[PDB]
Image (cartoon, coloured by chain):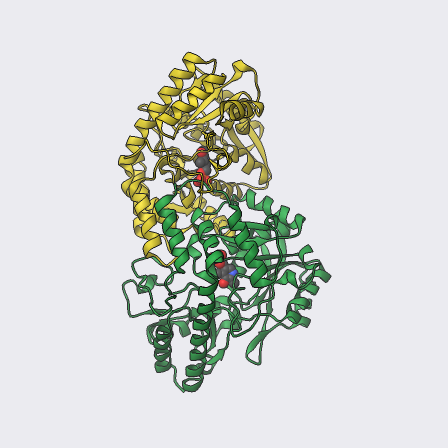
Chain colours: A yellow, B green
Amino acid sequence: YDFTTRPDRLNQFTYKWKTSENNPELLQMWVADMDFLPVPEIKEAIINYGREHIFGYNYFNDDLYQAVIDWERKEHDYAVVKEDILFIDGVVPAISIALQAFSEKGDAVLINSPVYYPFARTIRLNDHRLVENSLQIINGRFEIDFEQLEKDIIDNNVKIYLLCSPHNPGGRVWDNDDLIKIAELCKKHGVILVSDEIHQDLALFGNTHHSLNTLDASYKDFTIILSSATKTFNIAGTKNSFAIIQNESLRRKFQYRQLANNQHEVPTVGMIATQAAFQYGKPWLEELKTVIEGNIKLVIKELEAKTKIKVMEPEGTYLVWLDFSAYAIAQPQLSEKLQNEAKVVLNDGAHFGKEGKYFARLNVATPKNTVQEALSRIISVF
Amino acid sequence: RYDFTTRPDRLNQFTYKWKTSENNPELLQMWVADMDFLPVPEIKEAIINYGREHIFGYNYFNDDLYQAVIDWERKEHDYAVVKEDILFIDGVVPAISIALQAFSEKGDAVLINSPVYYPFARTIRLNDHRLVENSLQIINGRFEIDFEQLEKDIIDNNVKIYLLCSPHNPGGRVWDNDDLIKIAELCKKHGVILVSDEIHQDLALFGNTHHSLNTLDASYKDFTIILSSATKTFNIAGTKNSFAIIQNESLRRKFQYRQLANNQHEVPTVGMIATQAAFQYGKPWLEELKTVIEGNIKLVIKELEAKTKIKVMEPEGTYLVWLDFSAYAIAQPQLSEKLQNEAKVVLNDGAHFGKEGKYFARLNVATPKNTVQEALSRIISVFGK
């Protein structure tokens, strides 16, 4: 597979490279999609959709379900059946549905901050009290203060825990013990646990993603799993993802809200791409991990040697959380300095929470040579 | 040159329409509203090139897409809108959900004209809203609104949203200016928000003209939004892009807020591409389509009126024909069962659209003339004089 060609996406109206369209020298290393050529079989499947299909309505076929079932079993040791699997155009839509189906207006929803901005956004826009349990940085990785976490849950009468696993940013691939503690807190306090495991295929460095409901047969009583092929295989634009809800009561609640919002449908290209990704993508994924790891090592080595930036080594995901505290330039001025001076665009760390004021996130799902150029630019400034 | 004579074989393409034919190829599917025609050439090429050339990541709504919609609205519907007025959403029914949620309070009554597109009623009921069904009359071969009753329905039930289907499906009613004005004036008078589902707006036939609601009166945008799409027009429903036109800033902001809250603000890139291609290139295909649909409709009228007791409502628009089987006294769903089991043709169960559809079935004629002819001959052989 080809992980060296950085596709020219400047004329493809991409979110990632939009601001580079009239400024080609500007490197984009922010939003989480990849600058690699597509998985060959996925590309082939989408082309064949164009070549062969009438572009009308389609149903979710058995092969698509089977692809997800097989993926979940083989890649994550999670045995699910067809009825457990709900397709939805995206994980964040699924989060909206979960908030709306599993809690009442005003109910507190907890997240671990800093985290993927759409978490906080979606909680706020849905009239929920947002509870941000601040993660601690200990020995270069995020850790949960479980004493505070339980306090946050009790003090705020938290009804839903929106979990990011692996956690973005930071790339924390929670240990089994972490996840068990989380789940036990939810069980103890009658909290519904929504596990956003969209990065579940991107555990690196010998780390193992533990899908929440695989840990204990009781967890499915209050836990739903959200994931997708889109982060793993760079097919976000195809708009298909899945929720796995083994608890029938929770599942029907989710389905009702999904139908109420008319989010029960997804584009056929998303059915096709997800199926192709899971059916054929494993070998590509394995090579991707190697490339991503190589890129991360480059970031750590160069930034740690030539710079005062503190690098949080991802345990997973292809996104690197960078601590620019030493330079005392807060966001958004920090990201502006990176874009304007370094000519590299990183995510504004403040978007993920107050904790990210002096942080930026670097997307290394792009060829090594591009990561190298980005690093040299950053170093030339910082 | 376009092709409206080849009926594509969709049996191995996991289609909603032909699902029950996949192991029963004899069964003709003439129900759900997508078309059995080859795709618009330029749309197919656009989608093929998405596959060949894009990285399948995130995309934004580009200016050519907005312009395509702006130009389409102007040229095809005399509706001048700007980029800021246009919100993309994966579908019209999703936009309806957002409209209900953003433009009314918990439990508020929502009105529809029955019988109508089933997802209207379903979406209203599932969103904790009272379903007020204003029953359409059938007068001189088309639906007409009883405005006396309509006003009563609005007042007596404190209706907060009027979900309008224009053109109306089923029946294919392309409302007269007078009708739309009376509707809008009632909403204006009674503080009702009007959601105009104009997804069939490009499919007015025979010289009938669709009148997009807000073109009628500059004040209507204060309480009226327009929902439409390229998908019904160009048979690209699977690409999941459509648009809401909301010129009123407040309505627009409320809609966008809820759209974002539901995370329905993004659509698949293939839908962006397909919609843009449809509006940029599809006009000539559309014009030929209309003549094919018109021909099919005339064939349905001629054959069914001559050889059966089925009363045919001639569509003013849409490619869907509302058929009255009252004379045979077989009610739905036994009616559609008889059609499927004996005539080997699948038509929509009229009752799904409302109580008034008890003895009705809807025939989709967006398929080659020879296929319509086959369906007609089958129907006639089971339902005679």
Q: Which image quarter holds the N terminus of chain B? A: bottom left
Could you tell me which residue is drawn at 63 percent across and 47 percent down?
B254
Task: Using residue B369 as the reference point, say whether residue A342 is left or right of it.
Answer: right
Q: Position of residue B142 (x, y in %)?
A: 56, 76
Q: Is residue A314 above or below residue B192?
A: above
Q: Residue at x 55, y 67 (%)?
A: B167
Residue A118 position in % (x across, y down)? 52, 35
Q: Nearer the viewer, residue A84 or A261?
A: A261
- Image quadrant for the C terminus of chain B? bottom left
Above or below: residue B58 compared with residue A305 = below
Q: Is residue B149 found left or right of B166 in the rendered image?
A: right
Report the residue that reaches farthest toward the right. Answer: B189
The residue depicted at 46 percent of the width and 58 percent of the height is: B281
Is A184 or A206 nearer to us in this picture? A206
Image coordinates for residue A204, horizontal then vertical, percent: 34, 26
Instruction: Choose between B39 and A271: the one closer to the eye.
Output: B39
Residue A347 in view in this figure: yes
Q: Is residue A207 above or below residue B262?
A: above
Is residue A204 visible to the viewer in this orientation of the structure? no
Quadrant housing residue B337:
bottom left
Q: Position of residue B172 (x, y in %)?
A: 52, 70
